[PDB]
Image (spheres, coloured by chain):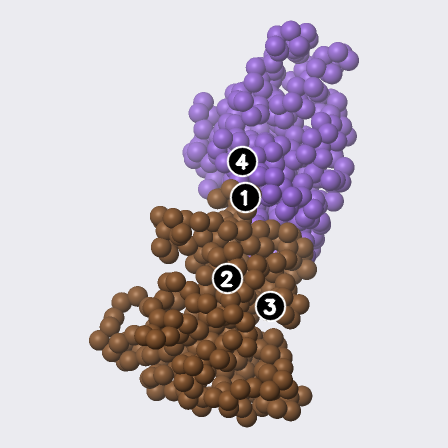
Chain colours: A purple, B brown
């Protein structure tokens, strides 16, 4: 049992798939070795972890994030004044543009080395509205048939940011506001990288599916017609409701998600309401089989 | 080359018109060998102006292999081997073989070939489409080929004359088959008899089979055969699919067919 497994923290799982609330820790202070090791263990098991009532400074946010690995900010997001490491998920009450992250994805997979983790802090959030969905890509992989696993385990996938800030984004109508989103170079948006379809997590050693509808373009070597149905099945499979959890935000909630083995989704159900969270990005290494 | 027959290909994919031979007479070794060569290359072959009897029809068919026939279709009186593709001028409704398929793939050993003979056909209307499953396989990307080559598919007649006993009986064929005569690899799926990819869930199997149906039935993999009276046609039941065109409402259409037995589809 978790009450006896963990001696320095208290862990309350959110679902039988992923997610856990962590209490009995003060993120304003440096964490001792035993407390940190328990947090990391919980992170590896539960994949998305959150800490209610953590009224921390920007510096304390950065210091906590550094325990997971180096700070490596994502290309697209604006940073707060004085803190280049601390980026914004900010939506004004009156704005009606495209919602950041309103499709199932994981962050910045177009990079050669996408983020390992993101640490998100609720600054000012609605009483209700603006939950974040998460899902386990371990579970998504583990629930495929043995035959389907054998069929796809050797495949590689082409990723790019073309639909987010590349040529395909610039061709369409649904645009982000300048609140949290930078103006970007089109060539950076179109730059392709190839990642494995199934990846091994370097911390847990576990295999997970690695595909997302936002950044994945096609299966490497296949035509668009060949790739489209296989990728579409995998999106529908991974995003099955039974593979998900739903996180409700409160002021001063600090959340860490694993950017390799989870996907996440914004919920745009708070029109007319201010929503502001900050985030630091933990650098990762090249996704590997 | 062709020294004993004249061969006119119909498209750059499949189909050929063969002339310079009389199918009423027995074929010598040299002529037969050339016909078989053309059959292996062109997959669907047709011979205009062959006013052959029922007996001559059977005799020609026997050169390709054993002549069965299949239990589903109705035989003409006096000739169990010779079966009817008949639609009266008064008749209207749903036509035999109006989706892309190949014959009786629910069997452990489906037919190798079918020999069709036009008796009374309209001036226009009632063409038969054919497509090459060699071409279907060959035009898949090397990556897609490698991905699906080891898959097997469950076939049954359950949607045709089963629950959805003999119709419910399942058989398993490879998704990609090697032709026992030509040695060439071809895709082997059809929407009429294929149920699922063996080992996969419904959600996994459905979109993959659906893509393969769409791919195989691409217009550029097809040919279209127009019928005339006394036209004799042979199709390869392993490496082709075919489709009847129901564009002859109110017109009489009559053809006979013999069925050549095959062996287990093999990788």
Mark 3 element type: helix
Residue B32, x across and y down, in percent: 59, 83
| First along the sequence among labels 3 and 1 | 3
Write the residue at 34% across / 75% down: B78
How far is disc 2 from disc 1 in space, using C-alphas?
24 Å
Q: Are marks 2 and 1 on the same chain?
A: yes
The residue that appears at 46% across and 42% down in the rendered structure is: A96
**Mark number displayed over residue B134:** 3
Q: CA distance from mark 1 to mark 4?
A: 29 Å
Q: Residue B197 appears at what percent x and percent y? A: 53, 49
Marks 3/2: CA–CA distance: 18 Å
Q: In which quarter of the view is residue A221 placed?
A: bottom right
Q: Chain of mark 3?
A: B
Q: Residue at x 60, y 14 (%)?
A: A11
Bin the neighbour count of mark 3 within 10 Å (Cα to Cα): few under 14, some 14-19, many 20 and up: many
Q: Nearer the viewer, residue A11 or A117?
A: A11
In the picture, the disc for residue A265 is 4
Foreground residue among A89 and A68:
A68
Give the chain of mark 4: A
Q: Kindly check if marks 3 and 1 are in contact, taking CB atoms under 8 A apart as contact.
A: no
Does residue B90 appear to the left or right of B122 in the view shown?
A: left
Say yes or no: labels 1 and 4 on the same chain: no
Point out residue B130 in the picture as x, y percentages from the top left corner. Answer: 49, 73
Asked if one can make out residue B265 in the rendered structure from this viewpoint, the answer is yes
Q: Is disc 4 placed on a helix, strand or loop?
A: strand
Whether labels 3 and 2 belong to a single chain: the reply is yes
The residue under label 2 is B110
């Amino acid at each position: 049992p978790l009450s006896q497994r963990f001696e320095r923290i208290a862990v309350q799982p959110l679902t039988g798939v992923l997610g856990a609330e962590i209490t009995g820790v003060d993120l304003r202070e440096p964490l001792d070795d035993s407390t940190w090791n328990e947090i990391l263990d919980a992170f590896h098991t539960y994949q998305v972890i959150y800490f209610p009532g953590q009224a921390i400074t920007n510096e304390q946010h950065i210091a906590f994030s550094r325990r997971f690995g180096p700070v490596d900010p994502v290309p697209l997001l604006k940073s707060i004044e004085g803190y280049p490491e601390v980026q914004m998920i900010r939506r004004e009450a009156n704005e009606s543009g495209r919602v950041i992250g309103d499709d199932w994805h994981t962050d910045s997979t177009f990079l050669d080395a996408p983020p390992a983790a993101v640490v998100m802090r609720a600054i000012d959030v609605p009483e209700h509205g603006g939950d974040t969905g998460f899902l386990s890509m371990y579970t998504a992989w583990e629930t495929l048939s043995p035959t389907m696993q054998a069929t796809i385990e050797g495949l590689n996938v082409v990723h790019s940011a073309t639909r987010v800030f590349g040529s395909l984004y610039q061709a369409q109508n649904r645009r982000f506001s300048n609140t949290s989103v930078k103006v970007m170079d089109v060539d950076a948006g179109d730059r392709e990288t190839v990642h494995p379809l199934v990846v091994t997590h370097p911390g847990s050693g576990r295999k997970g599916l690695y595909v997302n509808q936002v950044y994945c373009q096609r299966i490497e070597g296949m035509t668009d017609a060949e790739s489209k149905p296989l990728l579409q099945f995998l999106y529908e499979h991974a995003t099955r409701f039974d593979f998900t959890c739903r996180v409700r935000w409160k002021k001063d909630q600090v959340l860490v998600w694993d950017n390799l083995c989870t996907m996440h989704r914004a919920v745009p159900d708070y029109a007319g309401k201010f929503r502001y969270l900050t985030r630091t990005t933990v650098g990762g290494v090249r996704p590997a089989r």
